[PDB]
Image (spheres, coloured by chain):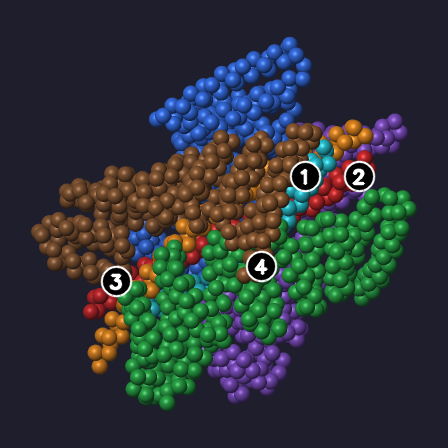
Chain colours: A cyan, B orange, C purple, D blue, E brown, F green, G red
Amino acid sequence: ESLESTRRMLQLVEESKDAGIRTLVMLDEQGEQLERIEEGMDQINKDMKEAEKNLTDLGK
Amino acid sequence: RADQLADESLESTRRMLQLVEESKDAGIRTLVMLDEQGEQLERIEEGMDQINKDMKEAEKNLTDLGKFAG
Amino acid sequence: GMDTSGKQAEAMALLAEAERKVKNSQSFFSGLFGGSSKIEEACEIYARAANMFKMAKNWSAAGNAFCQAAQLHLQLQSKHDAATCFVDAGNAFKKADPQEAINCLMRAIEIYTDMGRFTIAAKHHISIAEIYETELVDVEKAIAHYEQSADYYKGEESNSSANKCLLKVAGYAAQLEQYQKAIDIYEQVGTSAMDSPLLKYSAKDYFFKAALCHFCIDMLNAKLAVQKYEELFPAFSDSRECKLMKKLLEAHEEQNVDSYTESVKEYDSISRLDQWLTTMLLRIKKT
Amino acid sequence: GMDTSGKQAEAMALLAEAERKVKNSQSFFSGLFGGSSKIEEACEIYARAANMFKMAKNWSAAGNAFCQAAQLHLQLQSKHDAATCFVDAGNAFKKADPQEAINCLMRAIEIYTDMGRFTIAAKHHISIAEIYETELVDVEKAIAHYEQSADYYKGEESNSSANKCLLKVAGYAAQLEQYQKAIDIYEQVGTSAMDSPLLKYSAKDYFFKAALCHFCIDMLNAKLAVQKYEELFPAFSDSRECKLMKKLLEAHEEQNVDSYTESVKEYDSISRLDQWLTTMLLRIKKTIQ
Amino acid sequence: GMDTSGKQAEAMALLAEAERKVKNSQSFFSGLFGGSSKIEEACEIYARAANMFKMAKNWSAAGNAFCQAAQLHLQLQSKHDAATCFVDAGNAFKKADPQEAINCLMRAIEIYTDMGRFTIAAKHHISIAEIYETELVDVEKAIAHYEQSADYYKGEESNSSANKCLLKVAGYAAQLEQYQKAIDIYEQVGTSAMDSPLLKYSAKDYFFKAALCHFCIDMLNAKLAVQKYEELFPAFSDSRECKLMKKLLEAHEEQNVDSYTESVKEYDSISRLDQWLTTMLLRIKKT
Amino acid sequence: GMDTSGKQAEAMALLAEAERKVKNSQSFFSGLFGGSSKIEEACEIYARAANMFKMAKNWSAAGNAFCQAAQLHLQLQSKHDAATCFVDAGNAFKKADPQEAINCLMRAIEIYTDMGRFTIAAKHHISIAEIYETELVDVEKAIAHYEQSADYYKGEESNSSANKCLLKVAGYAAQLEQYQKAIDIYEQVGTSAMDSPLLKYSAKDYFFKAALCHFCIDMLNAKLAVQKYEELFPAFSDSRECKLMKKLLEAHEEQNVDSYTESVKEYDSISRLDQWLTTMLLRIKKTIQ
Amino acid sequence: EIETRHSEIIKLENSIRELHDMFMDMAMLVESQGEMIDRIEYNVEHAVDYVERAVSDTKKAVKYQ
C-alpha cells in the first residue's frame, strides 16, 4: 500500500512541477509587459501636462 | 540494520513534514496576495476608461466649437 | 429580444437615412459644403446601426455596417478610427464568414505598419495565423505570418513572445518534416532559456526535442549531438530524458523491437504522452 | 460623535444651500435664461453634499442626493455623468436599502447598452445578480442575469468569465431545475476545457458532476454517459471518481443500502464531501426502493 | 560628491534668484499690475529648487521649499498642485525630521477628503499610522489611524483592504491587554472567511487565535468558544490545532504544568512560533 | 527583397528632401519669417524617414536621423520629445555602435534627472550597466551604475529594486573586489528580511554567503561571525548549511584535505552546485598547506 | 514507529491533494489577469495615439490662427 502511495506521490509532485514551471513563465511575461505599459503611461502624462499648460499659457 | 532504517525514517518524516508546511504557508500567502492586485487593476480599468471617454468627448466638442468660431 | 429585432429593423432604417446622408453628398452638400460634420454624424449613425445589429446577433449585417462606416470615414482623415472600424468588422466576421475578416485585418496591418505600431500589427498577424489554423488548413501562410510577427517582436527586444512563436513554428515544421529549421530554433531557444535563472528548468525539454529531431535524420551523428548537449550542460544527463534517449539509441544498434518498446511503455507508465511525441516516435522507430 | 455632529451640521447647511440652488433653478428656467450653468453649479454642490453625506455614514441621504443630482443632470443633454451618478447612487444604496439600487442600476445598464460598452454592462449585470442572490431570496432572476452576463461575455470573446458564469448558473440550476441544462452546460464546459491545457486537469470534476446528474434521473442513461465520457476521455478511466461511480452503480443495481452507505462513507473519509454532493447523494439514495 | 557640491552651489544661487523673484514680482504687481504669471514662475522656481535640493541630498530644505511652494500655490487659489507639493514635502521629511511631515500629511488628507476622494486619504492615513508605529510608541494614534483607514476602505466596499487594517488593530489591541476588540475582530474576519473560495483554507487560523485570546479570561469560556467554533466549522477538528488546544485545556485543568510545557515545546519543534504567540502562551502559563 | 530596396531608396529621397527643406527653412526665416513650422515639419520628415529606415532593418543611419531630429527639436526649446528620441536612438544603436548608444543614453539620463524623474533615470542606469558588462568586459563602471540605480530607487522607497541591485553589486565585488563591502551588504540585506511577508525563510542563504566571505578572510573571523549569527538567528542553528560549514571548519582545522574533499563531494551529491560557491571553495582549498 | 509512518503518509496525501487544488486556482486566476492586462494594453496604446494626434492637430489649428 505504501508502494502505490509513493507512486501517487511521484505522479502528483511531477505534475505540480510541470504546471508550475508554466505558471512562472506566465508571471514573467506579465512582469515583462508591465514596464512597457508604465513607460507609455508616463510618456502620455508628460505630453498631456506640457501640451495643456502650453495651450493655457497661449490663451492669455 | 534496523538502526539506519529508523534513522533515515525519522529524517524522512521530519523533512517531509517541514517541507510540506513551508510549501503550504508559501502557497496560501501568495494566493491571498493575488486578490489585491486583482481589484487594483480592476479599478485602473474603470479610471482609465473614464479618462478615455471624457477626453474623447472634450476634444470632439472643442473641434466643433473651433469650426463654429472659424 | 423580438422588439430588439424590430429595432434592428429600424436600424436598417438608420442605415437608410445614412443613405439619405450620402444622397446629401450627391446633391445637397452643394449648399451644405461645410457639413463635413454632417458626414461625421452620418458615420456615427452608421457605427451605431452596426452596434445595434451586433447586439441583434446579425453578424453579416454588423460586419457590412462596420465595413461601410470604415470606408466612409477613411476620407484620408481620422485613419486610426478607420483602422478601429476595420478591426471591429474583422472581429464581427470572425464568426460566421471570416474570409473578408482576413482582408480587412491585412488593411489594418498595412495602416499600422505605415504608422509603425508593430505590437498591434504582430498580434493581428497571430490572430490571422490562428484563424487560418483553426478554420482553414493552410499552414504555410500561418508559418509566414508567425515569422513576420516574431521578427517584429524581436525588433523591439520582446524576446519571450518571439521565442514562443518560434517554438510553435518549429513544432509545425517538424510536423512538416523540415528538421534543419526545427533543430536550429530549438537549440536557439534552449541555449537562450538556459541563460537566465528564471527559465533554466525548461532547457531539458527543448534539448530533448532538438535531440529527437537531430536523431531523426542521421543515427550516427545523434550520439555526437547528445554528447555535445551533455558536455555543454553537465546537468542534462541526470534528466530522465537523456537516459531514455541513450537507451533508445544504444538499443537501435541491435535489431530488437522489444528493447525500445518496453522502454517507451515504461516511460509512458510514469506520465502520458502527447500526439506530437507519440506520432514522431511511431514514424521514426519504424526504421 | 462630535466629528459626526459637526459633519451632520454642515450637511444640513449644504442641504439648505442646495434647496436655495433648486430655487435658483426654477427661477432661471421660468424667470431667467441661461440657467443651465446655474443648475450645473447646483449639480456641483449637490455632488459635494452627497459625497459628504457618504462620509457622514448617512447612506440613505447620500443615495437620495445622488439620485436627485443625477435626475436633474439628465435634462442637460448629457448622458455619461448621468451614468456615473446613477452608478454612485446604486453603490450607496447597495447597503441599507438595495431595492431601488436595482432599479437605478438597470437604468445605468440601459444607458450603457444604448451607448455600446458591453463589458461594463456585463460586470454590472453580474453585480446585480450577486446582490440579488445574497440579499433577495429568489433565484430565477439570478439564472436570467447570469445568462445575460454570460451572453455578453462570450459575445465579446472574453471566454474565461463567460465559462465561469455558465458553470455557476448551470450548477445552481442543477439543484432546483431540470438537469438537462445542467448536463448540457457541464458537458460544454468540460469539452471546451479538454483541449485547453489550463483546465484539462480539472475537467474531470465537471465530467463527474455530469455523471451524477445523469444518475440522479436514471441508471442506464448514466451508464451510457459514463462509458461515452471515458471513451472520449481515456484518462478518465483511471480516475478514482470512475471507480467510485462504478462501485456506487453496481451497489445500486443490487439494492443494498449498507454497501452504498459504507462506500460513500469511505469516500468521505478521504478528502471531504460538499453540501451539494451530499444533497445529491441523499436525494439519489432516498429513491432506492 | 562633486556633483552634490555643485548642485548645492547653484541651489543657493537659485534660492537667491527665487527670493529676488518673489520680492520684485510683488513690487511689479504693486507698481504695474502685470497679473499673476510672475507668481506662477516663482512657484516653478521653488519647485525646481526643491527638486535639485533633493538631488543635492538635503531633505529638510527640500521639504521646506516644497511647503513654501505649496502654500504660495494654494494662496494662488489652486489645490491639486498644492496637495502634490504638500505630499512631496511630507515624503522629503519622512526621513530626517518626520514630525512636520505628520502635519503636512494631515493637511493633504484634509484637502483630499474635503474634495471627496477617499482611497488616497486612507493610504495617507495608513502611512501616518506606520510612521507613528515605526518611529514612536504612541500606539493609540496608530490604532486610531488604522481604524479610520479601515472604515474608509470598508465604506468604499474594499473589503480586502479593510481586513488587513482590522487584523492589525486586533493584534495591537490584544497586545495591550484588551481582548474584547480582538475577539470581535478575529471572530468577524473568521466568519467572513467561511465562504471565500480561496481564503477558506486559512479561515481556521484566525479562529485559533481567538480561542487562545479567549482563554486569557477563564477555562469554561474557552471550552464553550472552541466547541462553538468547531460546530460552526466542522473541519476545524481536522487540524492539529484543535488537538493542541484540547491538550492545553486538559493539562491546565489538573495543574499539569510539565506536560503543558513539553507539548508546547514539541509544537515549537515541529514548527517554530513567533514572539506574539510565545508571549501569549507564557502569559497564559503564568496561572 | 523589393520591400527593403524600396524602403532604402525612399529613405535616401526623404533624407535629401529633409536636408533641402531645412536649408530652405533657413532661407525662408529671413525671407518670409514664417515662425518655426518649417523646422517642425522638417523634424517630422526626419522622424518618418528614420522610423521607416529602422523598419528597412538598417539601424545606424536610423539612429543617426533620430539624433539629428532630436537635436534640431531641442534647438526649439523642446526637451522631453528630444529626450525620448534620444532614448529611441540609443536603443537603435544598441545593435549598431555601443559608444554612441551609451552617449545618447547618458544624455537622456542627465536630462531626465534634471526634469525630476528618478525611476526612469535608474532604469536607464541599469540598462547602461547591462550593455556595458554584457559585451564590454569591465565591472567597476557597472558597479557604479548599479549603485546609482539602487540609490535612486531607495530615494523613492523602492526597496525591492534597490535590494536586488545591492545584492548584485555585493556578489560582483565578492567575486573581484574586496570582501568587507560584500560582508556588509550581504549581512544587511539578509537581516533586513527577518520579518519578510513571503521570504521569512530566505535570509539564511545570505548569511551562509556572508559566512563564506568571512571564512575567505580568516578562520577566527569565520568562527566568531558564525557564532554571532548562531545567537542572532536561532533557525540558522538547524540549517543544513550550518552543519556543512561546521564540518568544513573542523576538517580544515586539522589539515586533512581528504575530509574537506569528501565533505564537498557529499554536499554536491545531495545538492547541485551554483558555480559561485565552487570557485570560493576551490580558493579556500588552495590554502590548506 | 510504523503507526507514526501511517499517520505521516495520510497527512502527506492530504497535503499533496490540497496543494494540487491551490495550484489549479493559482493558474486560473493568473490566466484571467493576463487576458485583462492585455485588453488594458490595447486600450492604453490607442489612447496614446489618439491623444498625441489630438495635441498635434490642436497646435496646428492654433498656428493657423
Query: Which of labels 3 and 1 is toward the front?
Result: 1
Q: Rounded to the nearest whole Å, what is the CA distance between mark 2 and mark 4?
A: 42 Å
Q: Are marks 4 and 1 on the same chain?
A: no
Task: Please report whichever mark, 4 or 3, sits nearer to the chain's N-terminal start.
Answer: 4
CA distance for labels 4 and 3: 55 Å
> Amino acid type of disc 4?
Asp
Helix, strand or loop at mark 2: helix
Residue positioned 26% across, 48% down in the render: E208
User: Residue A41: percent from the left, percent from the top?
Assistant: 61, 48
| Residue projecting furthest to the left | E254
Please state the horizontal and vertical placement of residue C128, each as a whole percent of the image: 68, 55
Q: What residue is rendered at 74% in x and 65% in y?
A: F59
Q: Residues within 10 Å of mark 4 (few under 14, many from 20)?
A: few
Proximity of marks 2 and 3: CB atoms separated by less than 8 Å: no
Q: Are marks 3 and 1 in contact (CB under 8 Å)?
A: no
| Residue found farthest to the right | F31
Q: Is residue D125 above or below residue F215?
A: above
Question: Chain ID for label 1?
Answer: A
The chain holding disc 3 is: E
Q: CA distance from mark 3 to mark 1?
A: 63 Å
Badge nearest the viewer, 4 or 1: 4
Disc 2 to disc 3, C-alpha distance: 77 Å
Between circles 2 and 4, the one closer to the viewer is 4
Q: Residue at x 41, y 28 (%)?
A: D57
**C-alpha gap between disc 4 and disc 1:** 34 Å
Judge whether F189 appears above or below D275 on screen.
below
C-alpha gap between disc 2 and disc 1: 15 Å
Mark 1, residue position:
A52
The dot on residue E270 is 3
Residue receiving disc 4: E3
Mark 1 surroundings within 10 Å by alpha-carbon count, few (fewer than 14), some (14 through 19), many (20 or more)? few
Residue that carries the numbered disc 2 in the rendered image: G63
